[PDB]
Length: 496
Ligand SMILES: C[C@H]1O[C@H](O[C@H]2[C@H](O)[C@@H](O)[C@H](O)O[C@@H]2CO)[C@H](O)[C@@H](O)[C@@H]1N[C@H]1C=C(CO)[C@@H](O[C@H]2O[C@H](CO)[C@@H](O[C@H]3O[C@H](C)[C@@H](N[C@H]4C=C(CO)[C@@H](O)[C@H](O)[C@H]4O)[C@H](O)[C@H]3O)[C@H](O)[C@H]2O)[C@H](O)[C@H]1O
Ligand SMILES: OC[C@H]1O[C@@H](O)[C@H](O)[C@@H](O)[C@@H]1O
Ligand SMILES: [Ca+2]
Ligand SMILES: [Cl-]
Image (cartoon, rainbow, N blue to C red; front, top):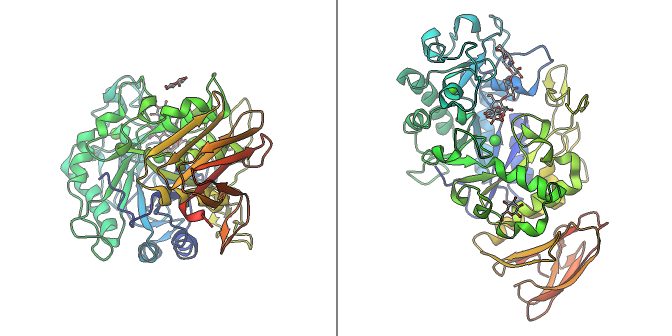
């Protein structure tokens, strides 16, 4: 459950948030495959309720009504086609499994669903599954409102309603089996693993019981006996009743402290400095590297939802975002996930974005295609961070230095920092308000390397900064505090 099951040499996955199956299929063949991306985390592929107020928000996909592969991203044919085409080019697919609940208990009975399935939230009727009143935790929840009134009580958070969502009685074998059948169908289709949504709201044992029923991965692409990759969404910033460690037996867990702390350090808040990152990782109180799935921001916290707060860096703060993603992709800690978002009209009234609900780029409800521009960027308001040179080249960097140990750390005692990875890569950062000009030990063999942050190595030339490393591994790095990208990165494969 801990092994990502990516094709050898590939070390990251991209969250193609709200993308349509057809666009992902294309993206796999034209970009993800050739650019060494390990895989893609897709949005919930099962049927959800249609929320008309507000107009088709992104969160309606987290309110299931059945397990039919039928959504705004596409139908089952399109889904199967995507998985096949992506696996065929070496890019795995990971599904966002929403299994702790069904739709909002307050939703209206009817066929206002993405596939037309009938459902009656009021009576807990979900005919298309099927689920009935006795498959929910209403009777087990002890709070007056039936909702989570305190996060200090493990029972409320797991047995009661998360924001009014109907809570599934996961201790029942019937429910356990319905969910397993859904996941098994996906596994057989070719999916490599899952993101267990809202794991914190389920007992580790219930998740385990479900996982034990899962099929081995499809042998058309995976070796016989391969277990699916599992990463559970557990928001634990420390100091709360439920600990992420309670889920280590099921698979990897989302380390939310990673993005919260990094954002604060890179922004230079609360007295934090980049020089403090020397012992980044478990030294900062994070979970063991091999149990962690790390990221800078995720679909929730980039828009105020979930956890992280104001410190979280997103594509909105492009410059700082790039250095944080670069640091993450360079550091050996955890399995990295890269975010890929869409632009929305933010509108902050009282420090709160009242438009945080806005769904993906659409034409009267139907999702717009991802258009690719000549300069390799995306149109139709898809930001495509994964296509930014600075990001795509760091994904490559991670592949290249995979397995090499953290080494040759250097810092100016403030915000200028540097470290390498064995003898295959080195990265330098300047987040101070002054010039960086030093001769540092890179640990790399002598030669001329193309900086992959400012450019690329084309044939036998660099399109950006070139770094000459002496026979003794040293090199000079000159980075101005006003540089567009205040960091340089070089590796074995960018060598001329
Ligand atoms: C979003 C994450 O919430 C929780 O994290 C909390 C941490 O546990 C806690 O430590 C931290 O301090 O605070 C966090 C919350 O800010 C979960 O632990 C975490 O798993 C969540 N992230 C996951 C999980 C979900 C749920 O599947 C997704 O949440 C989004 O989607 C829901 C559903 O669409 C959305 O809620 C909308 O719908 C419900 C029904 C509305 N609730 C109203 C309706 C009724 C009647 O049914 C009333 O009873 C309710 O009281 C009333 O509020 C919501 O108003 C509406 O927004 C969430 O807002 C979305 O965030 C996440 O996407 C997923 O990543
Ligand atoms: O050593 C790790 C610690 O270093 C301190 O200087 C920082 O302020 C802490 O946030 C961090 O956890
Ligand atoms: Ca629950
Ligand atoms: Cl997540």
